[PDB]
Length: 74
Image (cartoon, rainbow, N blue to C red; front, side):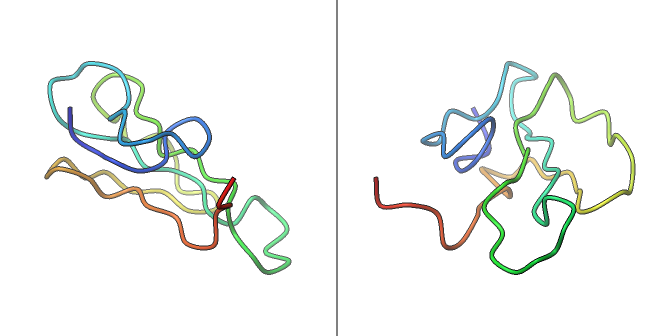
């Protein structure tokens, strides 16, 4: 119960696994930065282990912080 966005696809608030708040956010620019950007990770996977820098990454835990524009209305 935390991030209310992405997290293993379009999700729906899910808020990743347990950890009891928080949402590891990673990905955004796939790896081609060829425009767009709807292939993120921001999934959580415990307690946001931070992971690595690479493409895009972060770590929130304040209700959410792993959104994603564009998306698909279906």
